[PDB]
Image: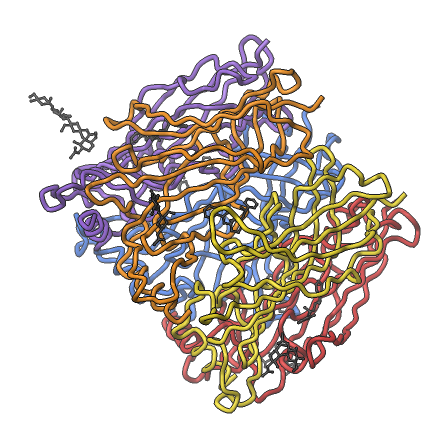
Chain colours: A purple, B orange, C yellow, D blue, E red
Amino acid sequence: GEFQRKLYKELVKNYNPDVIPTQRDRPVTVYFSLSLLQIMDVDEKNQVVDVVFWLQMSWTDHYLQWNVSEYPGVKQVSVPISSLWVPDLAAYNAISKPEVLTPQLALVNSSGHVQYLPSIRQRFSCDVSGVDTESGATCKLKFGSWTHHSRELDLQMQEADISGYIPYSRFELVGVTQKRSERFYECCKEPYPDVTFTVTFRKKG
Amino acid sequence: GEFQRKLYKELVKNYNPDVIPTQRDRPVTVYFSLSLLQIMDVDEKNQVVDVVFWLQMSWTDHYLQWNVSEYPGVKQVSVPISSLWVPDLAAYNAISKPEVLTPQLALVNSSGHVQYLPSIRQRFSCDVSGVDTESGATCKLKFGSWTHHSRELDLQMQEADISGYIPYSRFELVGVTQKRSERFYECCKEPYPDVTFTVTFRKKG
Amino acid sequence: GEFQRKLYKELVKNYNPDVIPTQRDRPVTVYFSLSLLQIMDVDEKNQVVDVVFWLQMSWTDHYLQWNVSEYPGVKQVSVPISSLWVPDLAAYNAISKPEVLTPQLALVNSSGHVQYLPSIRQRFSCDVSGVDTESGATCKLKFGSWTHHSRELDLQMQEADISGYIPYSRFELVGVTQKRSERFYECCKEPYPDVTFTVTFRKKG
Amino acid sequence: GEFQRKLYKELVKNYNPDVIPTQRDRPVTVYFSLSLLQIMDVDEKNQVVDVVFWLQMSWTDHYLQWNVSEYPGVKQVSVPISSLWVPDLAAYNAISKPEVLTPQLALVNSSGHVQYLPSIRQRFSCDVSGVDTESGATCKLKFGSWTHHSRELDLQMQEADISGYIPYSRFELVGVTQKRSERFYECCKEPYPDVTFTVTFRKKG
Amino acid sequence: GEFQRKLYKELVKNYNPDVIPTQRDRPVTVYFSLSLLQIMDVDEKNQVDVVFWLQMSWTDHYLQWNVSEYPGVKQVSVPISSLWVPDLAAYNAISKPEVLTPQLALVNSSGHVQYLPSIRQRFSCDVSGVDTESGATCKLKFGSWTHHSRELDLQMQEADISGYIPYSRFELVGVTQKRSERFYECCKEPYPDVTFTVTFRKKG
Ligand SMILES: *[C@@H]1O[C@H](CO)[C@@H](O[C@@H]2O[C@H](CO)[C@@H](O[C@@H]3O[C@H](CO)[C@@H](O)[C@H](O[C@H]4O[C@H](CO)[C@@H](O)[C@H](O)[C@@H]4O)[C@@H]3O)[C@H](O)[C@H]2NC(C)=O)[C@H](O)[C@H]1NC(C)=O
Ligand SMILES: *[C@@H]1O[C@H](CO)[C@@H](O[C@@H]2O[C@H](CO)[C@@H](O)[C@H](O)[C@H]2NC(C)=O)[C@H](O)[C@H]1NC(C)=O
Ligand SMILES: *[C@@H]1O[C@H](CO)[C@@H](O[C@@H]2O[C@H](CO)[C@@H](O)[C@H](O)[C@H]2NC(C)=O)[C@H](O)[C@H]1NC(C)=O
Ligand SMILES: *[C@@H]1O[C@H](CO)[C@@H](O[C@@H]2O[C@H](CO)[C@@H](O)[C@H](O)[C@H]2NC(C)=O)[C@H](O)[C@H]1NC(C)=O
Ligand SMILES: *[C@@H]1O[C@H](CO)[C@@H](O[C@@H]2O[C@H](CO)[C@@H](O)[C@H](O)[C@H]2NC(C)=O)[C@H](O)[C@H]1NC(C)=O
Ligand SMILES: CN1[C@@H](CC(=O)c2ccccc2)CCC[C@H]1C[C@H](O)c1ccccc1
Ligand SMILES: CN1[C@@H](CC(=O)c2ccccc2)CCC[C@H]1C[C@H](O)c1ccccc1
Ligand SMILES: CN1[C@@H](CC(=O)c2ccccc2)CCC[C@H]1C[C@H](O)c1ccccc1
Ligand SMILES: CN1[C@@H](CC(=O)c2ccccc2)CCC[C@H]1C[C@H](O)c1ccccc1
Ligand SMILES: CN1[C@@H](CC(=O)c2ccccc2)CCC[C@H]1C[C@H](O)c1ccccc1
């Protein structure tokens, strides 16, 4: 429709995707979830794990809301992420650039709530020593904002999800636990929240 | 291509390729089919298939129609996909980005019917255990829109053909099946359709 | 440079690189040749041949012509292919993207004749069964417009060249034949021409 | 506050990111530091070392400061590095392109002080012969500006950090030492500074 | 600096990087040299890998300024996007060049440009004699892909083997350089190429 086209036009007007959408007194709450899909490979020589996982990120961008009466049918839109602000979450212990497997698009409803849900393949540093033992190996996948502290970006975990782990992998996914931490570095005065997903796994047999 | 040069300007005038071209608010019906060309490799350790395949996607974009009496010779135009809306179809169980082998061009006729026919190479998660057996290994290649539900994008399948499959391959096709489904996700209130290409194959011998 | 600079401004003005420069009842004739330089590898398990070759494409684009008197001294210009229309030739049986090795520039003279001469590495589907037999293996490299039928794009062979084939190669180049075909598809009224290069080769024993 | 939005647009206004922000014929002082995270691999045949490290770069950009009373709650911004000048530091003995593992953003505070802190994977030419010996192997990681001399870009080093080295690597990090050098080249009229990080390491066992 | 900022603005004004800055209707003279830093690998089966420092320099008359008008500014560092660069091709490369260094050129007030990319690239070569005492000899052939010798005058400077790493498994026996001029039965004018010949053998 032309309404959806006017709306797309207006969402981008006077909008800078480099500007985190805070409102004074308020940090941007970003809800964050990682679903492990497949353990692609263990490098026992170089201490590396290769994983495929589904990230779920959502937050409210209040510069992106619209009155639905002015845009009758339009209740959500699908938008390329280059055109809006997205959390600068970094994989603290990645040793490779992420390979995004899915279309780089976000959903946005009329309250300005954004949902961005990439599927990603990425290699991480990990001690994979015990992978062929009963206890298994344990990898920490650690994520957090690279440039935004707690009072700018409040990173929130959502519940752990192993439901997506492929059942025919040569690795048995023993468990996944998660932890949110606020670290002080002393670059900065402010703490930076990070979310850590702890994956325990072992060779089947 | 004098009339052709005039047409190309009018088509891109006030056109936003981020916007799914609904009307009513009809879903855009998208016709989808996969023709399998070559099974490039099986990874029995990591459970992956490497395949080369030919997609056929077609849909009607109503903003892309013209009066043919106003452009005498012009029945059809060849257009970069970067300038028009294309379905955001994702391979749900891919573990690599799709590698597009063919020119990224679509054919558009005067009533707005678009055809995009890329040949593609891509790796998928798959249990390839029984590839040495006589019942062979079965891989599900699942495709669907990433951000559009049923009432926005009506994904319909067109019939499979295996005649494109290369005959001098080390794998033989034992079975092929396409099938459309409509599932709910924890996600959304609207169902999302998908098309699943199920292929069964084995080592020759 | 004085008139060259002004001429470059004019060639891109009112010019659309997406529009095939046909005229009513006049296809764009595209002269096309392949010169094999080296056979990098043969994959007998996966049925792939890895080749380096030089393509030579030439055609006339009447929108690219100019009056030499108006630009004295300027008889040809070197132009990035991104800025002019180029033939959308695809490698039909390629299983990888082409790796263009040379600068992506085309030479254009004042009557609009374009020459584009890329050196390319690409991998193709092929039955290399006979590579160690020295009746040899035979690969067919197949090329054609992906979106223009023969009354839009008139694909013409020119005599192939093997003088450039590497003499110290692991593989002995037995011979190369070329063939222009015109094939119909159940889809379209108009046939689509292709050029196929048949290369026969064998390991040096 | 929409003061962040106001500030960003002022920062990029009348600003060129290709221009090093010198004042008064005074050089831009760039403070530089390297923290070694992991030695991914040693290639003893081709004499290559593969490493992941964290660079710290900071400097003052006088064009990028703002009076904080004019933009109330804004004390620092997060900014894509393509919108501001950043040091063109190169690894002089790298044998691969640097792979940047983190978001390409820089922090900037109101007095124009910038912090850019990429984590990076890169391979370096290095004599890795002694890696099995007790004295280990020694690799110079040599960095400097590619195009700015001492009087434009005053490269200074802060102290390196081995506290980030992963404890479960197959290589023990014996030590990292750093040294700042400055030399004339016969090529150019002005001298160039460089910072070299000398890494000693051996195989556990 | 504010002088630099407004100088940059002026250099790119009306400037088209696609246009070889021929003046006059003589060539742009392009000075060209190669410094071998490391032989990374040989593929004796497929007959093929090196890391080298290219040096290129030429005058772009469009890029001159008067230093009186820009007091401090004697040279600037610009992205090579923003200016014309030689379309030099590696005639026998079998891979795309991986450019290791920042893509920046130096330009001085006379419009003299220096572009010194460090590059890793694979080349076709008969490496079969590599273990032998006579070694393997490889040719690295470079030249303009679209400009003939009266648009682009390719000239070679002396080669630098001082940068070759001493701890390589290959010993660098010798390097020579030659400028040639070839006519192709197609194109009126000749096209000049500079070819660096590299002889090297396995140590031990
Ligand atoms: C766009 O998507 C977002 C994400 O789904 C969506 O936002 C959510 O909206 C609901 C309802 O407006 C929010 O729920 C509210 O939160 C507060 C405190 O957190 C509660 O107090 C509210 O609660 C209720 O209890 C009342 C009793 O006094 C009842 O009368 C009332 O009915 C409520 O049951 C309320 O639940 C929710 O917090 C947000 N979530 C986020 C992450 O913001 C938004 O509505 C969508 N936009 C549109 C236009 O649909
Ligand atoms: C543009 O292409 C479409 C698809 O090939 C043509 O449409 C079909 O037309 C037949 C009869 O006209 C219908 O029975 C089908 O249901 C149509 N299919 C779809 C998907 O719409 C259409 O005729 C072409 N337009 C022109 C002007 O030739
Ligand atoms: C532009 O280039 C074309 C192609 O090289 C020139 O045309 C050829 O002209 C020769 C004689 O000059 C003929 O023998 C060939 O058969 C032509 N080839 C083709 C493909 O047409 C053309 O003359 C050039 N124009 C100018 C003004 O120099
Ligand atoms: C911007 O950041 C810089 C660097 O963090 C701040 O400066 C340092 O402050 C300490 C404490 O007074 C000094 O000892 C250092 O010498 C400063 N470093 C530099 C490079 O100047 C600076 O204060 C910040 N600006 C504002 C407005 O907060
Ligand atoms: C710009 O650079 C060129 C080359 O680096 C300078 O030119 C040269 O002048 C010296 C002595 O005057 C000669 O030995 C060189 O052979 C010259 N080289 C060339 C290419 O002409 C030139 O002077 C520089 N411009 C300024 C303003 O310093
Ligand atoms: C970037 N840094 C915080 C800011 C900060 O610490 C910092 C900033 C500037 C200078 C010095 C330190 C933000 C959150 C990430 C953290 C980075 C971590 O050290 C790190 C670096 C490299 C690999 C793994 C982890
Ligand atoms: C992408 N997602 C739906 C959209 C959506 O989930 C969603 C939308 C908005 C918010 C939260 C979730 C569209 C239909 C597919 C489904 C994805 C499937 O679970 C999936 C996830 C990861 C790998 C493979 C498959
Ligand atoms: C793309 N196709 C023709 C058009 C067409 O078929 C077509 C048109 C419209 C609708 C459906 C199909 C144009 C000429 C090329 C041909 C390609 C060949 O099929 C093919 C497909 C996959 C691998 C190798 C070859
Ligand atoms: C690039 N070079 C200087 C420029 C310059 O030398 C030069 C300039 C002009 C002409 C000839 C040489 C600038 C500062 C860095 C220095 C680097 C080193 O040379 C080098 C080159 C190649 C590989 C490793 C190291
Ligand atoms: C491309 N060719 C000249 C042009 C030309 O020959 C040519 C032009 C037009 C028509 C026919 C041939 C320009 C200068 C470079 C030269 C290169 C060499 O051919 C070549 C081709 C492929 C791989 C290696 C080398």
- Point 35% across, 52% down: residue: B84
Q: Is residue A23 above or below residue B70?
A: above
Residue at the spot 51% in from the left edge and 43% down from the top edge: D159
Question: Which of the pair A137/E142 is nearer the observer?
Answer: E142
Is residue D44 visible in this depiction of the protein? yes
Ligand 9 image-quadrant field: bottom right
Residue C102, given in percent of the width and then of the height, sits at: 63, 61
Q: Is D175 left, or right, of B33 in this rendering?
A: right
Q: Position of residue E7 (x, y in %)?
A: 41, 75
E170, A104: nearer the viewer: A104
Seen at 46% across and 55% down, the residue is D30
Q: Is residue C173 above or below residue E33?
A: above
Residue C188 as seen in the image, left or right of residue A9 = right
On the image, which quarter does residue E27 sit in? bottom right
**Quadrant of residue D172 within the rendered picture:** top right
- Quadrant holding the C terminus of chain D: top right
Q: Is residue E120 visible to the viewer in this orientation of the structure?
A: no
Question: How far across and down, in percent of the image, does residue A163 sit?
Answer: 40, 17
Q: Nearer the viewer, residue D10 or D87?
A: D10
Relative to residue E127, is residue E191 depicted above or below?
below
Residue B128 at x, y percent in the picture: 59, 21
- The quarter holding residue E146 reads bottom right
In the drawing, does residue D108 fall left or right of residue D6? right
How many dots with numbers? Answer: 0
Q: In the displayed image of the protein, which residue is found farthest to the left?
A: A69
Residue at x 23%, y 43% (from the top left corner): A21
